[PDB]
Amino acid sequence: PGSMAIDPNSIGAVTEPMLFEWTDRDTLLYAIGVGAGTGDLAFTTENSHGIDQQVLPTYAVICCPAFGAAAKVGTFNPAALLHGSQGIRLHAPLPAAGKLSVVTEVADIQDKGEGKNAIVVLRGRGCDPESGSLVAETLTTLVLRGQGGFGGARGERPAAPEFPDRHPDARIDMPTREDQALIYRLSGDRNPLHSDPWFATQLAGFPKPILHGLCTYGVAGRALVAELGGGVAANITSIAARFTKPVFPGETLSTVIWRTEPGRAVFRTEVAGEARVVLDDGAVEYVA
Amino acid sequence: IDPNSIGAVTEPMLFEWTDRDTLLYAIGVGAGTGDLAFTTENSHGIDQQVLPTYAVICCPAFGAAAKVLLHGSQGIRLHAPLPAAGKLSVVTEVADIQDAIVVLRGRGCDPESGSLVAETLTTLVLERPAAPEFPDRHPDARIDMPTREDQALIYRLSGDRNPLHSDPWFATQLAGFPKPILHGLCTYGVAGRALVAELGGGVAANITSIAARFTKPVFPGETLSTVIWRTEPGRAVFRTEVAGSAEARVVLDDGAVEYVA
Ligand SMILES: [Cl-]
Ligand SMILES: [Cl-]
Ligand SMILES: [Cl-]
């Protein structure tokens, strides 16, 4: 009776194309959502003198969400990212305003056994409707705590990235606002875990509402765009990370980065205390 | 500016909005985690309320310019609570051109019933009516509300993209300010919030009409201090000031409110 229904026969199941459309208001709102301000007007304005709007590449999680595919596997929440991971890959810049035809898919289902975890992997692909050309990909890895033993394949946990044994090449601090979740939720995730202290505590057990995991991911994304992409959105190709611990709005997010190989880096995001790691196993591909 | 245009009207326009819009507006005018009725829709035991100043967004008088704010004025009057999501049939009028001074009026009705929901009156500076009278005594209330340095970047997402408020280049090299300025309608909203708390009991519906004059500019990050006097039952007058660093700078003046208790 306490078991989660997980279809081990659903790997490969896919959703029909769904059109995601947005205007510049949305991409601007998202940018402010992940903490962009007066300091980077390319992300927070469209009509400033000598500055074309750029779109953060982590916006792929909103216009190309892999989420729809979860309904093929079971009825669990596709967006509960704790202990899970999120990856994005871009093949073109996302325009300030546009449309994508998004299809999703159950990429993988892993059964670690009764009283161990289920792992569900959802993959999103977004293409320009006219040309059919591939714009963005997303990968959402969900950990369903203790829900194994449903008749699935054991599988293989992917290799964690190698973190060089030295000091980080760069530490980018990004503050967050006490009210940040209230703006970030207007990019679509209205879950009251992030906005209602009643709910956050009475159902979820936290002293206060937690910041959206994807907001944290967007903040780390801004730090990576600055440090590795030269402040050029388009120069970040892929970003992946694992969500290890929750963040509270108002906490400062330190993204520690290591350049490993031309066009590649690894990272973590933490909150200075011993530091709490909140994003781990970060991996980035970028154009020099 | 043909002075022949008085009494001219635009054909009706449908203004439509969802909860995202009214929640965004409230955050635009500085509401936060301590104002869950205005900034959330699904918080336990709290129905979303819409700040009455949202009339300036859903009942815009500016349709009438084609037929023709600092230093200008804005008034609103509401006959019903604005709903979190909804729509209005809006019609705008050139109320008066003075000879440069242009007074535009908007009226928004419920499309199904044809019933009047909101009125707005927008005075643009390019008979001057009676200033309210302020009583010679210390205010009944002073309500201080901060703004964030990014306040204008949020507020502009309720429609007004004027680079005056967002682009440092435009503001300093063409418009004559030291840095971008906060939308006057934003300051008005912040004063709106002050009024709702002090005179409305936190119930935004309780504030029926607000009118004020924009006298000096505000910059994002400044604390706006609304000074309020209860005059006659169900009525009050106010100003909104930024505390000097010096004499306090008055940014909204001639403020008059009608509310219900
Ligand atoms: Cl910034
Ligand atoms: Cl939304
Ligand atoms: Cl807008």
Image (tube, coloured by chain):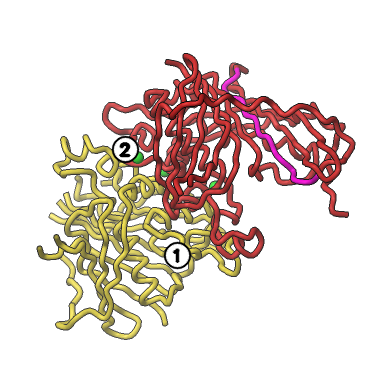
Chain colours: A red, B yellow
Note whether B192 is above or below B163 in the view shown: below
Q: Chain of mark 2?
A: A
Give, as a three-letter code, the residue at label 2. Gly
Nearer to us in this view, B100 or A124: A124
Where in the figure is residue A250, as x and y percent of width and height?
A: 43, 52
Residue A145 lies in the magenta stretch: yes
Q: Residue furthest left?
A: B246
Nearer to us in this view, B71 or A57: A57
For ligand 1, the image quadrant comes to: top left
CA distance separating discs 1 and 2 = 27 Å
Q: Is mark 1 within 8 Å of ligand 2?
A: no
**Quadrant of the rendered image containing residue B253:** bottom left
Mark 1 — residue? B34
Please identify the quadrant where the C terminus of chain A is shown: top left
Local secondary structure at mark 2: loop
Note whether B261 is above or below A176 in the view shown: below
Q: Is mark 2 within 8 Å of ligand 1?
A: yes
User: Start and end of the magenta stretch?
Assistant: A134-147
Q: Chain of mark 1?
A: B
| Side of A202 relative to B200 (left or right) | right
Same chain, marks 1 and 2?
no
